[PDB]
Length: 447
Ligand SMILES: *[C@@H]1O[C@H](CO[C@@H]2O[C@@H](C)[C@@H](O)[C@@H](O)[C@@H]2O)[C@@H](O[C@@H]2O[C@H](CO)[C@@H](O[C@@H]3O[C@H](CO[C@H]4O[C@H](CO)[C@@H](O)[C@H](O)[C@@H]4O)[C@@H](O)[C@H](O[C@H]4O[C@H](CO)[C@@H](O)[C@H](O)[C@@H]4O)[C@@H]3O)[C@H](O)[C@H]2NC(C)=O)[C@H](O)[C@H]1NC(C)=O
Ligand SMILES: *[C@@H]1O[C@H](CO)[C@@H](O[C@@H]2O[C@H](CO)[C@@H](O)[C@H](O)[C@H]2NC(C)=O)[C@H](O)[C@H]1NC(C)=O
Ligand SMILES: *[C@@H]1O[C@H](CO)[C@@H](O[C@@H]2O[C@H](CO)[C@@H](O)[C@H](O)[C@H]2NC(C)=O)[C@H](O)[C@H]1NC(C)=O
Ligand SMILES: *[C@@H]1O[C@H](CO)[C@@H](O)[C@H](O)[C@H]1NC(C)=O
Ligand SMILES: N[C@@H](Cc1ccc(O)cc1O)C(=O)O
Ligand SMILES: [Zn+2]
Ligand SMILES: [Zn+2]
Ligand SMILES: [Zn+2]
Ligand SMILES: [Zn+2]
Image (cartoon, rainbow, N blue to C red; front, top):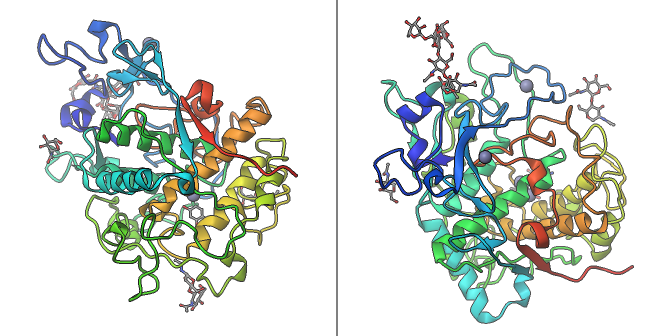
């Protein structure tokens, strides 16, 4: 989750993650591109405000007041610069001066030409096989991060797409208990609470940026899946897109799709929750997908209706107390899918984003594994298009987004876990076209 440069004994010892940009005069002489004016090494801001109660709750979780368990100094960039060392630009800008506005367009995957479709799944496949040039992932919790001999950082290289999967797993994993310790309350830094929409927003942005980097195609954009069709099939589960059903195992992907070759990460909950370890970069086992195949829950075998999207955009409040999966008249809880499309919570309703996950009846539905099915990307670009439309209709009314007593990870000014450099929910609560340099090509149901 941290730059390779910072995953060292010395940098953890200093508490400082301020890598060089262009260290012409030797190591440490252009931290954060300070010698060119691009940024400065400064103290991290981290939300201190209180969260909703948990029984029991030790507070030993390395995700509290993120990222302070590891670093308390990052790069703060000036102007429209950003990046872990301020070597790149804020979203929406390009150039060595970061002064050319760029605007990329995210579109319906089904609207793409045959050429762009092939480019997408090949780009996706590439990002699955290519080492992240920048981030490395911890395989051990903080108290063991430096190894048995105390001089060996427990960090692994990981692929671009697997990093996208890893960050999601880390945000939902259970707090370790140990030996003799009671069952700690279950927590979720990226679902069941207001930060769900902004966490996943940044999640996508980080993948888009990493893939534009990988391809050296600055305008590359992530497309989206309109799952609000009422359909009883998955209309992008074809061999020229996300993969059709295997004729040999009806829960596998057709061997004629590259995605049948993908192998998953983070599928060892039993190992982690007992050995005390974290998901690592070693893959094991294929994607399972079985659209409409959940015969035990008939509600989970059709997709959301088109009016479900239009109706949830009528919920005027962004979120409501207790800012949880049981909130009512809360647009966040509606689009996430724990309340019905009108606003009304019911513990039996599964709608929209949650409905779309369960529909897949496979790897795409398990909360710790779901990004391993690449349909995750396009399910979430769609969800984010709904978020972006809401932000527009209601001029980004951030007021009902709680500053405190939200579930842990979800306070308005929390640094979304485990993204780097630190980045608050507030920074994602903006219309995308003007403030984040992307927009959606989408028409909304007009009822
Ligand atoms: C920002 O981070 C700085 C770096 O700290 C690391 O990174 C952060 C993000 C965390 O991961 C942190 O745990 C990492 O260590 C941080 O500076 C560091 O602050 C710590 C905590 O105070 C310092 O450790 C303490 O040092 C004192 C005094 O130094 C003694 O040096 C020798 C060595 O033994 C002694 O013989 C002398 O008596 C010196 O006086 C120790 O008294 C103290 O030990 C006691 O406390 C610890 C827990 O803190 C217990 O385990 C012990 O048993 C003792 O009860 C600490 O070890 C550390 O030196 C310091 N490092 C540097 C490089 O400055 C900084 O404070 C953070 N800034 C902010 C604003 O929060
Ligand atoms: C996919 O759906 C199937 C069938 O709808 C699920 O397996 C059933 O789960 C129920 C409830 O837990 C069990 O009592 C049944 O024994 C299971 N049926 C069969 C035929 O195995 C399955 O868990 C779903 N998988 C995912 C990943 O969503
Ligand atoms: C939503 O779920 C929360 C969290 O479980 C519920 O809060 C509980 O409320 C009861 C009585 O009000 C307390 O005894 C529990 O300790 C609370 N749990 C926690 C974790 O704090 C709440 O009841 C639900 N809210 C609604 C509106 O139904
Ligand atoms: C990580 O990758 C970089 C280049 O991508 C390489 O220089 C380095 O040796 C790799 N690190 C490890 C720990 O294998
Ligand atoms: N109700 C489901 C919906 C869901 C949400 C997110 C996810 O990654 C996978 C999912 O399957 C759950 O909380 O497990
Ligand atoms: Zn706490
Ligand atoms: Zn600054
Ligand atoms: Zn998620
Ligand atoms: Zn999701």
